[PDB]
Image (tube, coloured by chain):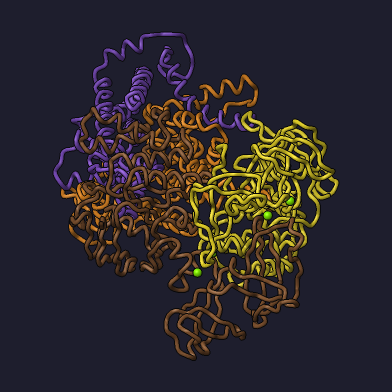
Chain colours: A brown, B purple, C orange, D yellow
């Protein structure tokens, strides 16, 4: 069931095409995250939906009703700002009741709704305090309660938890996901953080320079990238070069990678002489001894640096050709059999069917 | 201690003449140089003087009216500049800056020639217009400085919550800008009560204020009745400032 | 809403400030008349008369008298603003307010009070003799020194406030970085603080120099007939002799100086930002 | 011994920020002061730098007292959080300010400034104001300005906090290499634990103006001293236990959460004493269903599986009512991974790999 349908959205600001052309659909009852580098244009889409900006050309729907030109006062869309946009003189109670008062709500219902909204975010006893008497985590909850009390069809969040510390951010990442399920309305989130998007979202859209690169579930993004930018942006990847020699069967293809031959799993059709990119992640590579290898063929290289990062050990490995390859693994210092040698000939291997093959 | 002593010297510099004219009010000597006893005669003679009291009333009326109109126009202009973002804002700021940093003699003679090229008699209206003209920039600067210390996203937040513009200017901006409005009113009142140069150019015999009345008496000699007027004006001007803070609170 | 406020404020300024100024500059080029004031005859006699020695010595005297008053305000005003910036935030507004309380009494009465305070047989001469600092009475009335004392009195508050605003907007880490790198208090002032607060100095100078060249009641009451300011010259031509074109020619010199100081302000701001 | 602090106290607005602090900073090392927000690290840094005066105690630098010496006469330079960066000077003059203000002959100013700019890879941006540069450039200018006076100790105050995530990872290694190149001691104040683990040679943990632990990055993560340091550096699982008998000099039998197991204890204990057993989330294994005479020790249900990209966190619930929060890698293309949700499960560890606290 579609809720917002953007068709042919364009916008130009000061002789700059921020949004060339965008087609997007937002369903009902999900958590959606717009993620990308700085300056890709997520805030423009958010403001166009909210109504604080007007589109140069295109069409916008909400529940099969055209709101392209309806002003940003009659739409059923509410927004949470980055700076929390709080009125200083008003109290918490009046901050929450602002939207209800300017909707001509009957006076009898105002107090129970406001108290319920404050209870939803655990702030029922700070009703009569004012801002500047509250911490950041409290002001954020006041903003969310002010946005949610009008029963909107859609809630927009713009980098909401950016200014906070680590553990408090981790805890509110979970309360927001619980609140979305408790209410039952669509959330649209804009963030620059990768792990934050991967944790709390049910559908991720990656944006670069005003265009959509990939849309899918978090697993479909971290595990099956579509191009090189998406693979390198979320997570961290190793780029290998390949040339196709021959095909054995429908799903296994022989090719050389950096001067060594091994089998790779390719599903789409290829022809001999074609160049490919084989992508592997740090946690999927294994460094093993070659003196008693007697297992299979693999890459040869030396270990230059061993970095201790707490829970994980990151190793920088130099191949014979000269490309940098980095391997990650857990640190078990109480294991008697733990490799620690440096500047030695050791092999690099990976388990079959764990690669991501992308054509060029 | 040396830092505190320097600050006292500057305050003692400005306040000593006021103390002298307050004390010499009760002096019996007409010239005021020496001290020759305590008399109350000057206050009684002032009470029976008509032209002096009329001039004082005219000055106070001009001050109040000019302060009110300047406060209104400047507050509206400051809200206009702060609320919107447009291409012409630096130009308006520059014009206001140039108006503020201009000689008073040029501004007086320009208004004289303008009012003589339009056949407007010199009196109430010319004086009121001149005072408003040279009081506006300070009000604009005060209110703009006060408003720029707050986030501008609150207006967008009010829009998203379903508030029209007039509601936004009747519920958000005004309570945050009232203490600046009171200060603008007080500053304009002081500036209109202090000026001597413009008034001596753009006025006429029909409307007489304290500056030219005292200037006329200078050629003959200033009686200590003037000192008796200055001390009362201090108390009356004091309570007006006290009232303004309470109303704004 | 948006258009009404902008048109009214722009219409008010163009009608009352800018257009009349173009009338003054255009009046300096026409020809005098007894009953018609200005007559439409383009002449350059007005500007060339300013080069006569009689009317050129008066202009030179005013510049020296105003320049020293500006310097005296800067020397006594920068330390006052600096010390007010090292005080608790609650007491600062009260101290600033106590600078405009004297302004409620009119300016023409406060100079009259100061004249009595500085007279030969008045106070500040009896007290000094009683203390014994001086031996014979000090006579400074009707001298160039008296005018400069009076001008500093009236216009000192106008210089303090621009300087205090610039000082309070300074960044504390910038002052701490210099101290770390080996700067004495003197070298921090010459190389960091003064360049960062230069627009505040130029703003204060404009508000104290130009108004000090038009105060005619200081010269009349404290200076005499030998020590005159430009405002006395303009006043006579506009209200007693009724030679209006000459008054416009004299007032141009004040306008020309305004442009030079304004240009410094724009150039000082661009470099700083 | 470079800087020795003895009995330093400081009070600000009546509230104590440093009760009593003893510390020794050696020569040629990287030291990081790590702790929660508002614990008095910045006060220590400013006290060493000379921008604040102590209320009691002594500060020494190469066995000469510098308690009352002003900041201009100390051989310590500081990099500020906001990159002070005087706006009216070029980069060349910014770097040469300190040399110019110590009465240095004019022949040596240009080569020294050029070399300092070269060490931070800014030799070509010599004539540009500090508003045409980006964050990294400004940071490198600040570092070059600090290190051109040849100081005996460089102080850094949350230097790389405002940058992005990849530039941070690059400049951490860059600074770690620069320290070895120069040969002087660095003191760094940080709020991020990963930076302290990956960049430091000695970490000092502070809380409420007091020292909690001091040692190698390995020691803090692997051998915490009290319950605060664990759970601040990473995630911890605190299990209660009761000692029964001492099997030998190394292993002691105990009752953990109502079940018996053998644990390693390295100090004297007596039956009845209460013990704390701490285990990292990644050291715990949720193995197959309970097999007789194969796996024993704990019983619990999964109750959740959270996906976080590289790793997968499962918060299991025991029989008593406690969470355990197991962590592990996510291998999807491996055809034996378990996706079970709410049945009987087993919790084990490796008979060691545990930290026992008294
Ligand atoms: Mg481990
Ligand atoms: Mg896979
Ligand atoms: Mg995986
Ligand atoms: Mg261990």
Note whether A134 is above or below C264 in the view shown: above
Relative to D92, C223 lies left or right:
left
- Residue D170 left/right relative to A34: right
Residue B48 point in image, percent of width and height: 26, 13
* B62 and D5: which is toward the camera: D5
Q: Which quarter is ligand 3 in?
A: bottom right
The relative height of residue B149 versus residue C48 in the rendered view (above or below) is: above
**x then y, percent, for residue B180:** 36, 35
How many numbered circles are shown?
0
Residue drawn at 39 percent across, 42 percent down:
B150
Identity of the residue furthest to the front in this view: D292
In the rendered image, the residue lying farthest to the left is B119
Q: Position of residue C12 (x, y in %)?
A: 23, 47
Q: As rendered, which of C243 and D179 lies closer to the eye?
A: D179
The answer to whether residue C240 shows anywhere in this view is no
Inspect this view and state whether residue D162 appears: yes
Q: Quadrant of residue C211?
A: top left
Of the pair D44 and C143, the residue shown nearer to us: D44
Q: Nearer the viewer, residue A217 or B125?
A: A217
Q: With respect to residue B75, does D91 lie above or below?
A: below
Q: Residue at x 51, y 89 (%)?
A: A246
Q: Residue at x 60, y 64 (%)?
A: D91
Left or right: A146 with respect to D237? left
Residue A309 on image: x %, y %? 66, 58
């Amino acid at each position: 069931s579609p809720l917002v349908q953007l068709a042919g959205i364009r916008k130009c600001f000061d002789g700059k095409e921020v949004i060339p052309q965008l087609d997007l659909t937002i369903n009902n009852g999900e958590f959606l995250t717009l993620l990308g580098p700085s300056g890709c244009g997520k805030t423009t889409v958010l403001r166009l939906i909210a109504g604080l900006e007007t589109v140069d050309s295109g069409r916008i729907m909400l529940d099969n009703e055209d709101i392209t030109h309806v002003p940003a006062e009659n739409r059923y869309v509410n927004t949470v700002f980055q700076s929390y946009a709080l009125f200083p003189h008003m109290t918490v109670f009046e901050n929450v009741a602002f939207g209800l008062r300017m909707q001509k709500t009957p006076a009898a219902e105002i107090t129970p709704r406001v108290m319920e909204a404050l209870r939803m975010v655990q702030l029922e006893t700070f009703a009569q305090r004012k801002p500047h008497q509250l911490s950041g985590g409290q002001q954020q909850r006041v903003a969310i309660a002010r946005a949610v009390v009008n029963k909107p069809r859609l809630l927009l969040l713009d980098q909401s938890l950016s200014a906070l510390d680590y553990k408090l951010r981790k805890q509110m990442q979970n309360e927001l996901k619980a609140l979305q399920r408790k209410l039952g309305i669509t959330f649209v989130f804009v963030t620059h953080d990768q792990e934050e998007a991967l944790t709390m979202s049910d559908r991720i859209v990656v944006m670069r320079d005003g265009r959509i690169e990939q849309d899918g579930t978090p697993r479909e993004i971290y595990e099956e990238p579509k191009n090189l930018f998406v693979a390198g942006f979320i997570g961290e990847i190793n780029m290998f070069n390949a040339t196709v020699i021959e095909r054995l069967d429908e799903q296994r293809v022989r090719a050389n990678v950096e001067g060594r031959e091994c089998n790779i799993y390719v599903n789409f059709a290829v022809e001999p002489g074609q160049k490919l990119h084989v992508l592997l992640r740090p946690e999927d590579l294994r460094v093993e001894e070659i003196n008693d290898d007697n297992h299979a063929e693999g890459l040869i290289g030396y270990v230059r640096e061993r970095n201790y990062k707490g829970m994980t050990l990151e190793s920088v490995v130099e191949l014979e050709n000269g490309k940098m390859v980095m391997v990650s693994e857990f640190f078990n210092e109480d294991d008697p059999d733990f490799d620690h040698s440096l500047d030695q000939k050791m092999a690099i291997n990976w388990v079959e069917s764990w690669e991501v093959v992308l054509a060029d | 201690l040396l830092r505190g002593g320097f600050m006292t010297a500057i305050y003692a510099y400005l306040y000593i003449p006021i103390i002298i004219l307050i004390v010499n009010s009760f002096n019996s000597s007409r010239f005021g140089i020496n001290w020759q006893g305590f008399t109350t005669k000057w206050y009684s003679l002032l009470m029976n003087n008509d032209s002096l009291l009329q001039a004082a009333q005219h000055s106070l009326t001009m001050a109040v009216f000019s302060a009110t109109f300047a406060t209104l126009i400047g507050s509206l202009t400051a809200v206009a500049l702060y609320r919107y973002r447009f291409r012409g804002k630096p130009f308006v700021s520059g014009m206001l800056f140039v108006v503020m940093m201009s000689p008073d003699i040029v501004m007086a003679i320009s208004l004289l020639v303008l009012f003589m090229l339009l056949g407007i008699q010199l009196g109430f209206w010319s004086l009121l217009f001149s005072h408003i003209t040279f009081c506006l920039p300070f009000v604009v600067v005060t209110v703009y400085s006060r408003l720029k210390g707050f986030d501008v996203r609150m207006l967008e937040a009010a829009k998203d919550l379903g508030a029209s513009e007039f509601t936004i200017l009747r519920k958000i901006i005004l309570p945050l800008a009232m203490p600046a409005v009171a200060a603008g009113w007080v500053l304009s009142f002081t500036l209109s009560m202090d000026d001597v140069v413009v008034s001596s150019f753009v006025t006429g015999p029909s409307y007489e204020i304290l500056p030219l009345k005292i200037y006329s008496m200078v050629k003959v000699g200033v009686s200590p009745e003037v000192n008796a007027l200055a001390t009362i004006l201090l108390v009356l001007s004091l309570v007006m400032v006290i009232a303004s803070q309470l109303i704004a609170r | 809403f948006q258009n009404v406020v902008i048109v009214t404020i722009v219409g008010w300024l163009v009608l009352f400030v800018f257009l009349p100024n173009l009338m003054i500059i255009g009046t300096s080029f026409l020809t005098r008349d007894d009953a018609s004031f200005v007559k439409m005859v383009f002449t350059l006699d007005n500007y060339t008369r300013l080069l006569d020695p009689l009317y050129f010595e008066v202009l030179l005297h005013s510049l020296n008298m105003a320049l020293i008053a500006t310097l005296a305000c800067l020397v006594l005003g920068y330390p006052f603003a600096w010390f007010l910036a090292k005080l608790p935030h609650k007491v600062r507004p009260l101290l600033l307010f106590l600078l405009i309380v004297p302004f409620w009494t009119n300016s023409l009465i406060r100079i009259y009070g100061l004249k009595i305070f500085l007279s030969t047989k008045g106070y500040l001469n009896e007290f000094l003799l009683w203390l014994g600092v001086i031996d014979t009475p000090i006579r400074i009335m009707f001298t160039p020194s008296a005018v400069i004392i009076g001008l500093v009195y009236i216009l000192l508050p106008f210089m303090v406030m621009p300087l205090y605003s610039s000082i309070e907007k300074l960044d504390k880490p910038l002052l701490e970085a210099a101290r770390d790198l080996g700067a004495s208090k003197l070298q921090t002032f010459i190389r960091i603080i003064i360049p960062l607060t230069m627009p505040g100095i130029i703003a204060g100078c404009l508000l104290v120099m130009l108004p000090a060249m038009g105060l005619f009641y200081v010269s009349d009451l404290m200076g005499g007939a030998k020590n005159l300011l430009i405002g006395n010259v303009i006043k006579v031509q506009f209200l007693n002799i009724r030679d209006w074109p000459f008054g416009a020619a004299t007032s141009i010199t004040l306008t020309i100086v305004m442009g030079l100081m304004l240009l410094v302000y724009w150039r000082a701001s661009r470099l700083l930002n």
